[PDB]
Amino acid sequence: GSHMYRHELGMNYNFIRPDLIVGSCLQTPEDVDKLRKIGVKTIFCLQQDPDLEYFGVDISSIQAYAKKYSDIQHIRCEIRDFDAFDLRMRLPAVVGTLYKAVKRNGGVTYVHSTAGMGRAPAVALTYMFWVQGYKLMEAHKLLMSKRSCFPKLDAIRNATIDILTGLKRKTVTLTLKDKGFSRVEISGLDIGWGQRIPLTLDKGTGFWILKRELPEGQFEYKYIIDGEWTHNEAEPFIGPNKDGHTNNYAKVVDDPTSVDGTTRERLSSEDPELLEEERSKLIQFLETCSEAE
Ligand SMILES: OC[C@H]1O[C@H](O[C@H]2[C@H](O)[C@@H](O)[C@@H](O[C@H]3[C@H](O)[C@@H](O)[C@@H](O[C@H]4[C@H](O)[C@@H](O)[C@@H](O[C@H]5[C@H](O)[C@@H](O)[C@@H](O[C@H]6[C@H](O)[C@@H](O)[C@@H](O)O[C@@H]6CO)O[C@@H]5CO)O[C@@H]4CO)O[C@@H]3CO)O[C@@H]2CO)[C@H](O)[C@@H](O)[C@@H]1O
Ligand SMILES: [Mg+2]
């Protein structure tokens, strides 16, 4: 559903494995005590400051409290909420940080976001996939059975491809016929659903235009026309989705017949089978990542 997080019911979480918890945000310094009691040695926080300010959480008091103890480490590795693109872009570095933390700290690892429904499950699932050796859909089935969430499989598949093959960007042009509009924006795409970017009305063209450089993948977006959310009937669209919403999408493709394009196709299937040389390459990347601080 649309609004499932209930901050007032306090920090909540599930063991995915005995050594790996996915949970919602710590709310008070005393929540550090709760995690120490179950053998948590790393608190891996994905929230940004506005997420914390929205719910009145004082992250500084939590960090200061955790520093009193030598048997738990609090780490901030920030990812924007409601932004599958930022998630795709951040996953490699974030999982690298987590990889180094778990190696150094051991015990139980507590991976959290605001709700523990999007970013934290995505990060934990990517860690199970790249580090712990699970097949992606094997880990996904396990995760979904332990905690109801929305773990952003498309972001994970794309981050994996980004590490293995690199990012190739091209100019994408989105356009909307004017019907006496004062303002036209797009949300979603590469900026997230919490953000909007204005289009320009072409002088004497009768059309609003946006040009953006995007890497390969499929990007859902929607127009805001004088403040009203609208999908453009003249561009590709998908839905209604679960939540009853229809979005436009931009499908960006480099070259399907190339070696990298052939790899992308294999890794974009539901359960992307990694070669062992690809697993070794993911670990090589993680090993280069700097430790928290
Ligand atoms: O942090 C502040 C925030 O906290 C709470 O949010 C948390 C929430 O309670 C909890 O459930 C969770 O959210 C989940 C969510 O439940 C899942 O459904 C899921 O959401 C994604 C959704 O399934 C995707 O479709 C997507 O939605 C886009 C649509 O695709 C767009 O079309 C667009 O929708 C607009 C629509 O088109 C218009 O016709 C009009 O109806 O307006 C809509 C916009 O309001 O935008 C939405 C996104 O807004 O993307 C969704 C996000 O990925 O996955 C979620 C977790 O990722 O976790 C929340 C914290 O992350 C609290 O309830 C909120 O009130 C508060 O703002
Ligand atoms: Mg190459």
Image (spheres, helix red, strand yellow):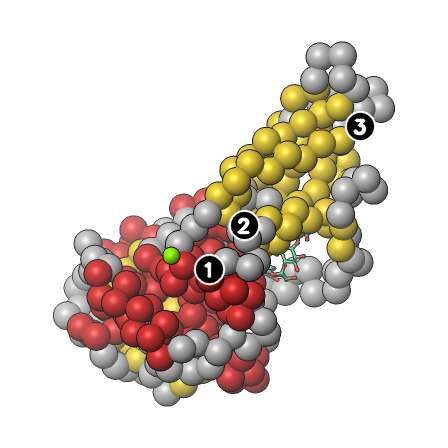
Q: Residue at x 55, y 36 (%)?
A: 171
Q: Relative to 13, is 77 above or below?
A: above
Q: Residue at x 76, y 17 (%)?
A: 205
Q: Relative to 230, is 277 above or below?
A: below
Q: Residue at x 38, y 63 (%)?
A: 164
Q: Which residue is mark 1?
A: 260
Q: Earlier in the sequence, mark 1 or mark 3?
A: 3
Q: Which residue is mark 2?
A: 254
Q: In which quadrant of the rendered image does the N terminus lie?
A: bottom right
Give whichever of 99, 212 is nearer the camera: 212
Q: Amino acid at mark 3?
A: Lys
Q: Quadrant of residue 70?
A: bottom left
Query: Closer to the camera: disc 3 or disc 2?
Result: 2
Give whichever of 14, 235 is nearer the camera: 235
Q: Which residue is mark 3?
A: 177
Q: Residues within 10 Å of mark 2 (few under 14, many from 20)?
A: some
Q: Amino acid at mark 1?
A: Asp
Residue 243: image location, x then y, percent: 75, 60
Q: Are marks 2 and 1 in contact (CB under 8 Å)?
A: yes
Q: Amino acid at mark 2?
A: Asp
Q: CA distance from mark 1 to mark 3?
A: 36 Å
Q: Earlier in the sequence, mark 2 or mark 1?
A: 2
